[PDB]
Length: 223
Ligand SMILES: NC(=[NH2+])c1ccc(N)cc1
Ligand SMILES: [Ca+2]
Image (cartoon, rainbow, N blue to C red; front, side):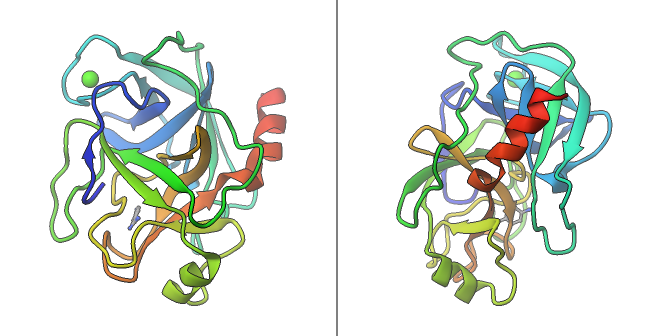
């Protein structure tokens, strides 16, 4: 997260870190046994880390649970990033409490103008690299489809939305992928892609979660 702020320990209780020996992506806990992330975060041997603030220090509220299965969206295209969504099932149910909590799926798609909270442990620099150890946060509005498409000609599908600031300086970034965009207490987006990070006229592009609620529910019901 570039140009954000320190969230505060366990203030984003649905935020998970995906770990394969090291943090590599974010995710969102949507019930005691399932995490939503980005398909481009797929790999084998994932350990889900809940209750995390400093990802390099055991602070006392962590739950580390290996994934039993991952399900990449059936129509995920890695070239265009269309349908950049996957589900990860935990081998055991997490223990839910105030610091480790699921986030609700949307009942309705969020509109341009709605303020959301974006969070992650990704790069905090637009130029060069610095990874924070604690969770970073950014409040950002959903942008209009027209401004999104104008910013990225020929690249924005009906399964994507832009959020952030056209002026630049405030954005998600590498390492934030798969993490949440939460608006009015609902998971509306997944950190997906963008040109660099926090660049002028290159806002963040996010998977449009509301399009996937049926697939998510049906997938969970049978797996
Ligand atoms: N929002 C962004 N600029 C972004 C997010 C993730 C990513 N992998 C690349 C760029
Ligand atoms: Ca920790």
